[PDB]
Structure formats: structure tokens, C-alpha cells
Length: 121
Image 1 (cartoon, rainbow, N blue to C red):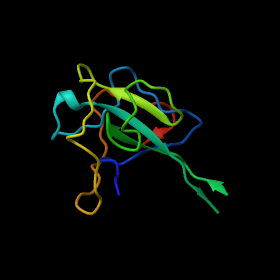
Image 2: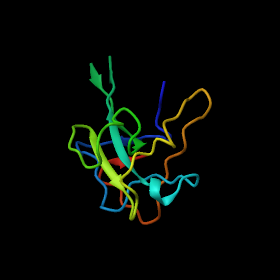
Image 3: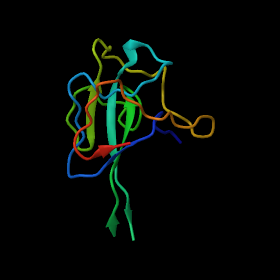
Image 4: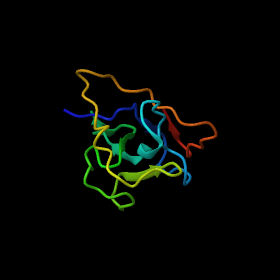
């Protein structure tokens, strides 16, 4: 099974995640500036049905459950982020995580990043 490389953002409001134009890409010192572009995918969970808080997981462009999705496409539960000068190419070489060999990276955002209302890590 596959997984995000990073820990997910939890939603504490009726808001749909959305960053300012140049923010949102989680830090990863082991990737190049060309690779800093992807999407957050919302994951819902119900429990007893009581609906839990939605979590958003980041996947590099061209990987993850929506690997075939071009950057910018409009789909429910998919929002896009990219930092200045990233390449609009699939990041197949980074891929997705296998929890059997690697644990998730703690999601961190660059300094001066503004998280929207009701979103925390």
C-alpha cells in the first residue's frame, strides 16, 4: 500500500483548504526546488454515523491517488499548491511512501506561511 510522505493537516471548520499562491508545499530537505509542487487530498472518516474531522495529505504532482491529475484541475477534495519556480512535471522519482520501510515526515511549512482558518497539524 502507498501513503503520503508527510503527516496530514486536520480541518476544524467548514473551510476547504487553500493556501496563498506560493505556499503550502511541505519542507523536504531531500528534494530539489523543481519538485516542490503537488496537491492535498482530503480524507474523511466516520465513526459510531458521527463524522470526524477531515484530514488533508500532500502528494507530489504526478504521484498518489490522483497521480494522473494535471496540476490545476478542479476536483472535489483536491487542492493544489506549488512554490515559486517549481516544474510542472510528474515527480515519479520521489513516489509515494511505503509505511513498512519509512514513517511519515512531520509536515512543516516554510516561515511566514499562513494556514487558513480552522487548519492545524
